[PDB]
């Protein structure tokens, strides 16, 4: 019902994308 990304899915996706986001100032 309510979950699209499990803990590992989010932790992978979220953190990797976080880094992508971070590079916007580089």
Image (cartoon, helix red, strand yellow):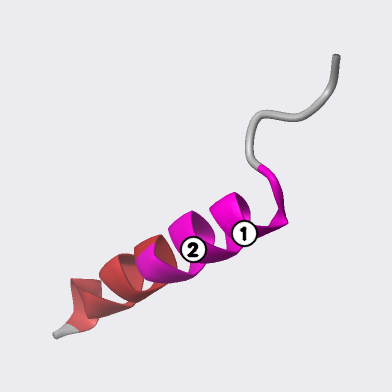
Marks 2 & 1, CB-CB < 8 Å contact: yes
In depth, the one of 12 and 18 nearer the eye is: 12
- In the current view of this chain or complex, which residue is farthest to the right? 1
> Which residue is the site of mark 2?
12
User: Residue at position x 63%, y 39% from top?
Assistant: 5
User: Residue at position x 85%, y 14% from top?
Assistant: 1
User: In the rendered view of the protein, which quadrant contains the C terminus?
Assistant: bottom left
Q: Residues within 10 Å of mark 2 (few under 14, many from 20)?
A: few
Q: Helix, strand or loop at disc 2? A: helix
Q: Residue 1, relative to residue 23: is it above or below?
A: above
State how far apart marks 2 and 1 are (Cα).
6 Å
> Which residue is the site of mark 1?
8
Percent of width and height locating residue 25: 21, 81
User: Residue at position x 56%, y 51% from top?
Assistant: 9
- In the current view of this chain or complex, which residue is farthest to the top? 1
Q: Residue 6, relative to residue 7: is it above or below?
A: above
Q: What kind of secondary structure does the magenta stretch mostly adopt?
A: helix
Q: What segment is highlighted magenta in the picture? A: 6-16
Q: Is residue 8 magenta?
A: yes
Percent of width and height locating residue 16: 38, 68
In depth, the one of 26 and 12 nearer the eye is: 12
State left or right for residue 12 relative to residue 19: right
Mark sitting on residue 21: none
In depth, the one of 12 and 15 nearer the eye is: 12
């Amino acid at each position: 019902k309510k979950k699209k990304q499990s803990w590992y899915a989010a932790a992978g996706d979220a953190i990797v994308s976080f880094g992508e986001g971070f590079l916007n100032a580089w």
